[PDB]
Length: 452
Ligand SMILES: Cc1cc2c(cc1C)N(C[C@H](O)[C@H](O)[C@H](O)COP(=O)(O)OP(=O)(O)OC[C@H]1O[C@@H](n3cnc4c(N)ncnc43)[C@H](O)[C@@H]1O)c1[nH]c(=O)[nH]c(=O)c1N2
Ligand SMILES: CCCCCCCCCCCCCCCCCC(=O)O[C@@H](COC(=O)CCCCCCCCCCCCCCC)COP(=O)(O)OC[C@H](O)CO
Image 1: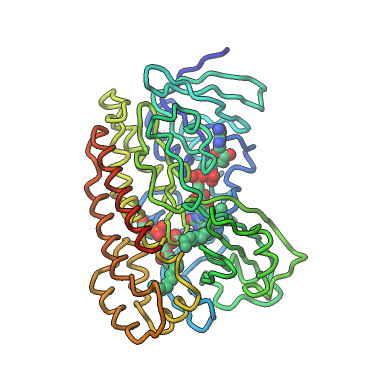
Image 2: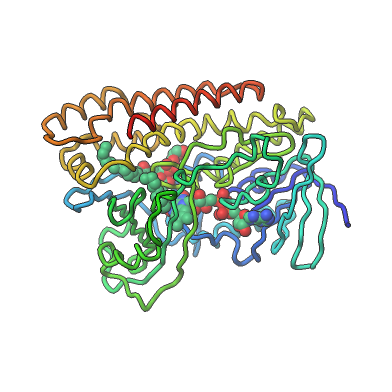
């Protein structure tokens, strides 16, 4: 079999892999990115397509333009289950044509020196003497099986986790997730019969009956075009998401023309803290494969880009030291936990609480202003729920005359702070990963028990 020598092999070309490729480009490295999809479909996984402008501003990722930017977003309207209370949170973002933008990032990375093979699947790892050393690839364009050696593999395969899952199970880089730590989500893009009101605002509808463990959304892509969908928690035995969608669509999108559909589809999305380590010998894991998604709102394209940024940084350092061991690549973890992962861990706790609340709880808490809109934003963006804000919340609901999980909010805030602190003390070397992981697991185990 043909053998080729590369510095870096990136497996997957979605927002995570493409970000890694772009950030590593123009540096004189020999880089190959592969994706199983044909070029014109790369980036087309089902998504709401909404991403904060701040991510592009912080990471130096190409700004969306032309047909790539479908609609400018100025904020989100969050609806209570009874739709009687709407919270508005302001913030600039983009409703993107995801495949078009993703493909442009890849084409620019390619112009900047990255080699790209589409219709090419990494079939199995090359794993020797404890290191990932590359991959066996099947290129369906040229109909060739190829062995590619690399100093580092960037595993960016999305939820499939289709490369790292083939490594020896004792390695921390093969970590799986609980079925209840992901949602299944489904969306369609449709034209509307009536102009969309406040089309610069996304709509998110909380409802435990119509989207248990997730939410419904209505994300305008123009004055007369909308991405509408829902997510529901996995591992709970819920019926087909397609059936939830059909049953409740009219509640959230009475205005759509069901004869003018542009796209439809679903996929899984992780909703938890990141992989305990995103680095091991010869390999870094990013994006959905590394569980980079915000656990409370389900947004993962921004954090995918952050993970690509951190991967590129760690890889450049490893080429300086010549050390591609877990320790040599460990900055991946330090960078990612600082930039997003510690917040994710806090939000993993908060999500578990929110998923257990009843519609009556959410209606009451929103109507009574249990927390401010700005407090919700602080939780979403920093992962902080200050003990103070918790105290005010408890005073607000002190008149509630029935049993409610809402009264546990102070304890939830305490657990959030505790896990955030553990993440701010992320292990400085692989030798401490195990004991730290057990501490985190214990916090989660105890927290789960507190809600049962
Ligand atoms: C319905 C729905 C709705 C939303 C969202 C998800 C879902 C399912 N999310 C989450 C967001 O879509 C998601 O987190 C990112 O797109 C993940 O990007 P990745 O690059 O990690 O994976 P992604 O899955 O996009 O890419 C993985 C790539 O790897 C390739 N691949 C896999 N195995 C391979 C192999 N062995 N060899 C070669 N190639 C391989 C695949 O072909 C694919 O192109 C979201 N996020 C957000 O920010 N805003 C939102 O509006 C939403 N809404
Ligand atoms: C409930 C858990 C599962 C939910 C997931 C369901 C499935 C989701 C599938 C669809 C996902 C759509 C994703 C939409 C993303 C929005 C755009 C976005 O990126 O978010 C921005 C932020 O917008 C928001 O803050 C959204 C807030 C709404 C969150 C929804 C919470 C619902 C629960 C609240 C109810 C309150 C009830 C009161 C009771 C206490 C900022 O981006 P960022 O958070 O990644 O980071 C920015 C910063 O630079 C950090 O680097």
